[PDB]
Amino acid sequence: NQYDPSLLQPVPRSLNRNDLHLSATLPFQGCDIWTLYELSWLNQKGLPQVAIGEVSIPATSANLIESKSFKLYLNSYNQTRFASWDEVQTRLVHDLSACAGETVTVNVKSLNEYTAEPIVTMQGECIDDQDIEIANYEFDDALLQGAAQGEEVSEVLHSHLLKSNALITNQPDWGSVEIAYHGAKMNREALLRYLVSFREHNEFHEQCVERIFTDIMRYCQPQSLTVYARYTRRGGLDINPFRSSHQSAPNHNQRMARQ
Amino acid sequence: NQYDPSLLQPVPRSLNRNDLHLSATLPFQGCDIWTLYELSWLNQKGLPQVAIGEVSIPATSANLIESKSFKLYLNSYNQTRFASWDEVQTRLVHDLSACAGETVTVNVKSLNEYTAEPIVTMQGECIDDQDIEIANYEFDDALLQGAAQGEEVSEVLHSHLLKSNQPDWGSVEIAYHGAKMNREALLRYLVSFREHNEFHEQCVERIFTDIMRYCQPQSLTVYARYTRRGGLDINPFRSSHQSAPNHNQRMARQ
Ligand SMILES: Nc1nc2[nH]cnc2c(=O)[nH]1
Image 1: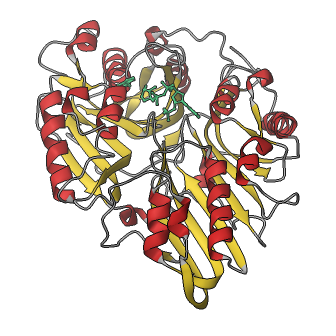
Image 2: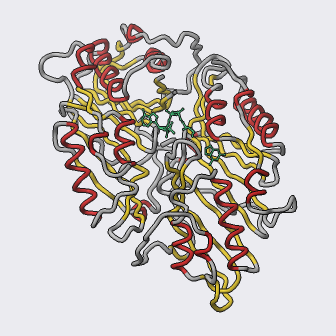
Image 3: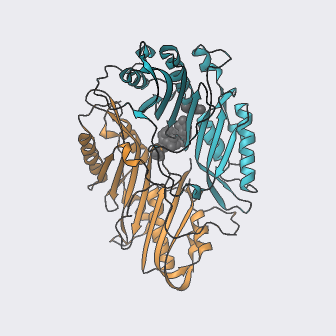
């Protein structure tokens, strides 16, 4: 019914990081960018307000925020009066920061900030148009074995074919992913097979991006690497994890066709 | 599970129209436009394909399609191999038309068709920025009693404050010619959908029939655009005189 920060449920980043054989000292930096498409509350006189929230959670935070719990938390604003949009911003930053364990950035944007904003696609070369046969759908990181044997390049690749399954109901998540790197040129077929092999994998979006980054790192050994995925929303919220050897945030945050 | 048209759930439109007490002949025409943001399947060689679908269901169809069922039906494509994009489009038309009871149109578009496409707002004047107090969110059609007493005008009004109890969210565009409508009454009435249950198509038909009966405009269009639930959205359009909106461009929350 009313505003309730206890609805937020953290999940520690360490669970999956330990599974990736990472140390406490991360091989990447970055953030999880969230879009809150249904943020709504009442003003001081009870008249509903609507906005889109843009949130960034540092990748160094102890916890990620579980997405269903984030949805239920936001729903608790819907019948609650707040003094001003600034109060809503302040409450979001306080609660989300406490749950994540590190200061989170929050922008609460009016809907008119999006009028005539264009849908974007990703940068560089799309690798999806390949005339190849897929014979099974089991996850296989060894699809990247020997995948980076070309000359030294800097380039940006992307795919729209990322899909994994949510941990419990096997309901699908959908994403596009952009991979920018400097290192030995990557075999496009290997990279595309590797990404397609997530199609029945169960992991959070943040975990998926970390696994792609660490698997490219270990098998392809680029000198620099950035992996940025943009997923379609679930429960009115989307996640867009960014992980980079050198960059701390993406220099653009614009929605894709399916988002 | 793979392709399964039995997952689709039709709901007779008469089920909820009965409670509107309509004449024998429908007082509106129009359509329900759906956007399918998560449409994906496998090609013949097993490589995933992704697309966005656009569906228009005539408001005269015997049935609407229940949204959860529509989502589960579309998910059944995800691990199914199809020979071509044209086959996918063809089966969508066939299955959704059989469900609705009337021919539906379906476009299956590659993601590239959306690059640079705009996010849009609605036409006319937004009525949401009022200095009024609302405290009682109960549904109350009587809020429209005597709402249209102004001189004869043509105008278009919109609100982003539709919410219909998990919550669903929409914006709604009302174009009319008739006695000028009191914007406070209209906003209170729309906000009163808040706590209250009905399908999105049902809310648009209730808004149309209530405006028709309380305000008596000579002509009227009511068009709502709801945010997606489960990867697809619905955009019901009802009018005394027009058949459809001019495009299906998405709004900021969609
Ligand atoms: N943060 C987060 N929470 C989830 N809950 C279900 N899936 C996810 C996910 O990918 N990320």
